[PDB]
Image (tube, grey):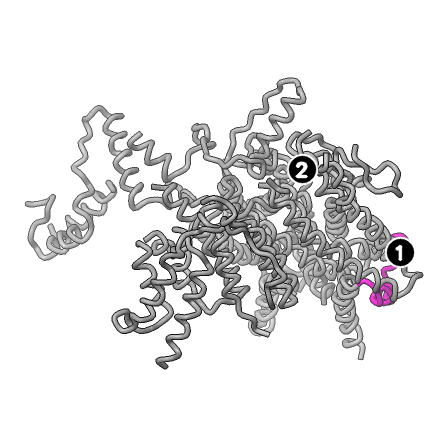
Amino acid sequence: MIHELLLALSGYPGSIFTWNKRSGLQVSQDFPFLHPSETSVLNRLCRLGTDYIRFTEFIEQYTGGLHGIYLRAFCTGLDSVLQPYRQALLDLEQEFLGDPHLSISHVNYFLDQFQLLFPSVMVVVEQIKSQKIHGCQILETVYKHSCGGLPPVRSALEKILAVCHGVMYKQLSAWM
Amino acid sequence: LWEAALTYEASKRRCWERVGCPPGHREEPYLTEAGRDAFDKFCRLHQGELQLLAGGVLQAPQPVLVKECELVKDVLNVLIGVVSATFSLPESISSLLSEVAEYGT
Amino acid sequence: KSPNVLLQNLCCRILGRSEADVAQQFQYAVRVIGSNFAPTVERDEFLVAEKIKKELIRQRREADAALFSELHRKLHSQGVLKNKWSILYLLLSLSEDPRSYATLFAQALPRDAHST
Amino acid sequence: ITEAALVRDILYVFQGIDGKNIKMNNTENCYKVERSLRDTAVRLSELGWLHNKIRRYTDQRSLDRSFGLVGQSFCAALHQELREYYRLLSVLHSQLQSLT
Amino acid sequence: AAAAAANLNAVRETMDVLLEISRILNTGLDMETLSICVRLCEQGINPEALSSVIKELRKATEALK
Amino acid sequence: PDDRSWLEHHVVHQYWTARPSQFPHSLHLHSNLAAVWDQHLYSSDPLYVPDDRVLVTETQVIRETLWLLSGVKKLFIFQLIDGKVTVRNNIIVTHLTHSCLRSVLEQIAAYGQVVFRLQEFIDEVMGPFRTYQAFMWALYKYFISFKEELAEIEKCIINTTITLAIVVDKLAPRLSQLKVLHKVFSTGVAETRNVVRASHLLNTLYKAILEYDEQTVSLLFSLWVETVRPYLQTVDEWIVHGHLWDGAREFIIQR
């Protein structure tokens, strides 16, 4: 159960947290083993996994109208921000092996900071798709969101921005 | 005594089927990696099966016992010129044994 | 072991010296552990839990004061200790501050108002 | 009614999640019960009633960039304060498996 | 048998929890002395009695140094 | 009993030799989840419909999948459809109620097909071209190093806490590299003369490195040198011996 969610949150939904692109990780299943209001706790928790699942597909399709080496730096940067989301999923299941008494809320508070990262990088992934940007001006539109106002997405965009600069420093090293 | 014994090693083997600190039982290796004991049992079972499938008309001369070093000393002795423990003027040991016996012969 | 030899093992833990050397202190220890030995007052672990919280507030450290709560829960989850009150009282008394008074702060009931 | 039924809803109405027999029909007024132990419950539920305001305000103002860097820093300060409350509520869950 | 080691495991856990408690309040005692103290507290003892003893016995070893 | 007892103990024998698994449990939902959901399904009145799967343990799956992933074929798990391994829907683990399992085992089956087809291709060269032979040799030279790391992990299984998310994450830089040769082989199966069938492949390889001009670039480079080797041999010979020889025409120049 507290391994099943750790895959429903990862990439493998299940029949209790069934996947839809019009509702991510739907739980509507009546539980004699859970309280009626536990479903809402699960509802708040499932948004965090929904974002990660969308991100992984977006990275998965590369390598539509978006093409270039710019998406071969952006998606690589999108992996690196999800890397502490892989380590911090590893840690919970390591804890659950000995102590099974740890409730949903432990996952809730421990992964509260990536429910701040995820909605503010979701707008970055949608922004490049609604209007097609695949030129050298991807850096400006990440560079104006790098100002931020929320500190997790303030430091996440630095990681991706350095990688974009690193790809720009090969064109401008052959050329020069 | 109990607190003296308490400083002992605790298991690092957990499961997602047995939850709540299982002690461990092991990972159960197969019959290509669990031998040096199940090897001997497997040979014994195979020999008994062959003797059943023939009718007792087969008669293994116990191609195991003696072990290795005694066998190695015996085949060292047949090359000197003096006779071995099966010839005088695992069951695949017979094939290896004939080839090194006829040398000293 | 028995307690009488166990107090000697304590006298050999804290002092490095042999027990045939230091026997005046072992004699002073045996008077005070004896005749005031067993619990005679009411045990309550919750007040001691809140006083471990008050000690950690006296350091102004609120994170370990919330870590103590899950440790205090785990002590009851296993349940293999006879006196949970004693060891927390003991460890609270033996605290050391790296870097008040108790005549306004109310303690446990003595069972001197209650029949033994 | 058993008290263990009440305690379960109580531990959720702090977050802003209505329990099974604790609901809030008029959103302004605090959580209303759907003999002394019955009287205590409203004073206990006030904290979650405040938590709703605080959570809902920082929900909206964090996503606004026409409100500036300052204001988003207020949101950050609020999110960090909100994080510790759930660490407390975790401990309150775990003590089930009295509890008054 | 096996359950007689499973309870040994169930106390082996608790001896770590009291160790974490003991270190975050920082006694000047270590695990081995602490084993004597938990052995004492199993039979039933007053911490108001025992702690005073510890405060005296620590003032006997830096009086011979 | 007396030999079956020893067999049952130290060797497993429980889904792949008929012996219904009585594996002990601690129940209580976090590892009882399939049973919890089945009881819930029955109590809601399905109506009836007993689902029959034969109940493998957890670690056995992971070990079997390792042997599948390394490059050897024909295991008991994973129903094949033509030579394409798919998820087996006749087994079940104590929790996850066979749905999350159906997803993740499908992921590893997707990797298993890519390795199955490549190893079968390499086998069918031993039962010349002078370029296919170097090509399979480069593929093989990758595969031996890849297989070694899988095998040492499988050795270290017997020597702790094992679940899916460790061995999946640990093999990320291997299943990433596996995806590339799928693309390289997709144009190697798209085919008259051997010189164009070599040159069209080789120029794709020569351009794919400059596309990413890491771990990928070393993979492409290590394949590149072992396939440009025969042409360097022939041009070296063309200079120094003053003659030209190929094994049935490795060039477009008719001298």
Residue A161 percent location from the top left of the image: 78, 67
* Residue at x 35%, y 44% (from the top left corner): B34
Residue F55 visible: yes
Residue F72 visible: no
Q: Quadrant of the N terminus of chain F?
A: top left
* Residue at x 66%, y 18% (from the top left corner): F47
**Nearer to us: label 2 or label 1:** 2
Between the C-alphas of marks 2 and 1, the distance is 34 Å
Instruction: Say whether marks 2 and 1 touch (CB < 8 Å).
Output: no
Mark 1 chain: A
Tag on residue A14?
A: 2
Range of magenta residues = A129-150
The residue lying toward the viewer, choosing from F66 and A49, is A49
The residue lying toward the viewer, choosing from E43 and F241, is E43
Q: Which residue is mark 1?
A: A132
Q: Was residue A132 drawn as part of the magenta stretch in this picture?
A: yes
F252 left or right of C69 in image: right
